[PDB]
Image: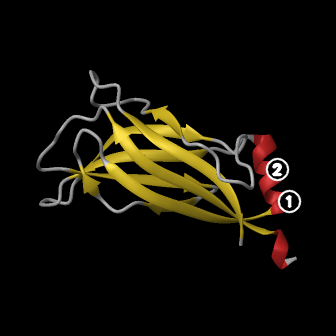
Amino acid sequence: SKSDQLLIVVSILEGRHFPKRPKHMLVVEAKFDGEQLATDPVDHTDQPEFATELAWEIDRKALHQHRLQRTPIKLQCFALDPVTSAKETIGYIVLDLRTAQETKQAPKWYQLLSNKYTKFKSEIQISIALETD
C-alpha cells in the first residue's frame, strides 16, 4: 500500500501587518497529531517572508478520519531574540483538513489569534495540500 502513503503539506508563505521589530526574528511552529515542525527564523519585518513547506506523513484511512474528526493543525507564532535565544508567543492559527485536496490550491489569509501585538491585524498566508508519499 505504498501508494496509500500521503503527505499533508502546509505552505506558509508571507505575513502582513506585523510590527517592524529590528532586533527580532519570527518562527512558526506547527503541531499535528503530536508531531512538531518549525520554520527557519525570518526577519521580523512588517511583511515577514516565511516561504516554507511543512510535511507530515499519514495513511489515507488515517487522513479521512482526521478530516471528519476535525483534528487541528495548530500553528504557533513566536518572536525570537537571536541574541538571548528567548522566544515569546505572539499568537496562534488553527487549520483543519477540510479543504485539503490532492491538488495545489490558492492560499488564504489567516489572522493570528490571541495576538500579542494588540493593535496590529497581523496575518499569515497559508496553503494546505495533499501529496503522494
Q: Which residue is mark 1?
A: 61
Marks 2 and 1 in Cβ contact (< 8 Å): yes
Q: Which mark is residue 110?
A: none
In the image, residue 116 sits, relative to residue 40, either above or below, namely above
Q: Left of 59 or right of it: where is 82?
A: left
The foreground one among 126 and 59 is: 126
Amino acid type of the residue that numbered disc 1 sits on in the rendered structure:
Lys
Q: Could you say which quadrant of the image residue 119 lies in? A: top left
Q: Left of 8 or right of it: where is 122?
A: left
Q: Which residue is mark 2?
A: 65
- Residue at point 46%, 41% (across, down): 125
Q: Quadrant of the C terminus?
A: bottom right
The foreground one among 30 and 122 is: 122
The foreground one among 69 and 57 is: 57
- Residue at point 23%, 47% (across, down): 44
Q: Could you say which quadrant of the image residue 94 lies in? A: top right
In the image, residue 65 sits, relative to residue 99, either above or below, namely below
Q: Identify the residue at the far top of this view.
A: 119
Q: Left of 132 or right of it: where is 72?
A: left
Amino acid type of the residue that numbered disc 2 sits on in the rendered structure:
Gln
Q: Secondary structure at mark 2?
A: helix
- Residue at point 44%, 30% (across, down): 113
Q: How is the image coloured?
A: secondary structure
Where is residue 79? Give x, y as percent: 26, 47
Q: Secondary structure at mark 1?
A: helix
Where is residue 129? Give x, y as percent: 66, 53
- Residue at point 18%, 54% (across, down): 81
